[PDB]
Image 1 (cartoon, rainbow, N blue to C red):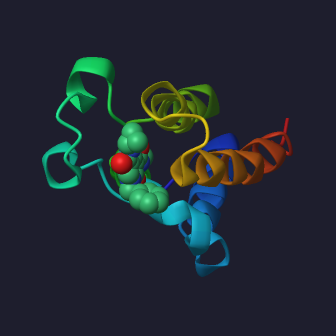
Image 2 (cartoon, rainbow, N blue to C red):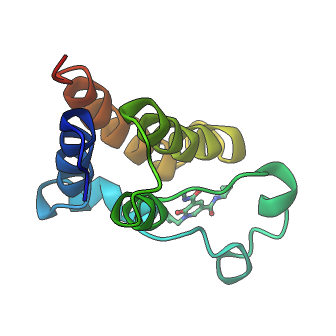
Length: 112
Ligand SMILES: CNC(=O)c1cc(C(=O)NC2CC2)cn(Cc2ccccc2)c1=O
């Protein structure tokens, strides 16, 4: 988990993004995109830096993130990858937009 006050807020957000409350739209972001399994044979040609919430959780648990900004960059990279790869009318993009709304509104409540 987070040690710094701001990293504890980040860890709180991460726990919320992984909670049953948001599972209906969070689930595509729980684990790395399995490009082979999903038939997305161009995924790793288009997405140079895959990211997902299990990777963010591992990095938080390993004290990889030194500040809130570094944590937020990985969460936003995950959404950006979704918006880059997927047609904007795909269900996964609607789910990304909803989960990013949850993220951005709570990230904005960061303690100073
Ligand atoms: C981060 N996830 C992805 O980018 C992703 C891409 C595609 C996908 O098939 N994308 C192609 C480009 C349309 C499929 N799923 C599963 C899914 C998700 C939501 C509804 C149905 C299926 C994903 O999670």
